[PDB]
Image (cartoon, one colour):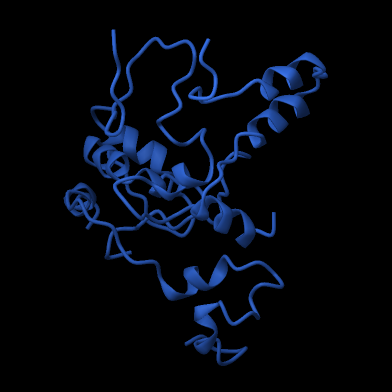
Length: 49
Length: 49
Length: 49
Length: 49
C-alpha cells in the first residue's frame, strides 16, 4: 500500500464527504436549525452513529 | 473607457484614494471582491457573515 | 525529488501541495478538482487509510 | 486565506470549484491587469488580439 498511492490517485473521480465531516461545518447556533440534514444521526454523546 | 462592462468599477479607485496604508486595507480590498449571486449569498449567510 | 515518494496517510500530514509536487498524478488529481486543494483535512485519503 | 471560506468552500456544482462562486479572486474570469503567463484553463474565456 505504500507505493500504490499514485495508483489510487490515477482515478479521476471525487469521493462523497464522510457523514462526520459533513456534520462538522455547521456554525455554532445554526446546527440546531432544521436545515441541518445530519441531525437525525447525532444520537448519542458517548458514541457516534 | 467603457466602464459598465468592466469587471472592477470606480468605487474601488475612490476607496483607494482615501486608503490608509495598514495591511488591513489590502485585506478589506480583498473582502470587497465578494461576489453577488444566489450561491455566493447562501455561502456567505451559512457562515453568518 | 527523483528518489522520493509521497504518502499522505494520517488525519494530519496530508498537504495537497507537497504530495502534488512530489508526484505528477496527484497534480492531475488536484488540477481536475481545484476545491480539494485544502489544508484543513478532507483532502481525500487513499481508500486504505 | 481570507478571500475564501476555508471551512465551507469544498464541493462542486459544475466543472468549476465552489470557491469560484463565492469570491471573484478564486474565479478565473478575473484576469489581473498585468500578466506574464497564460492560465492553464480558459473554458468560459476567449481573448482577442
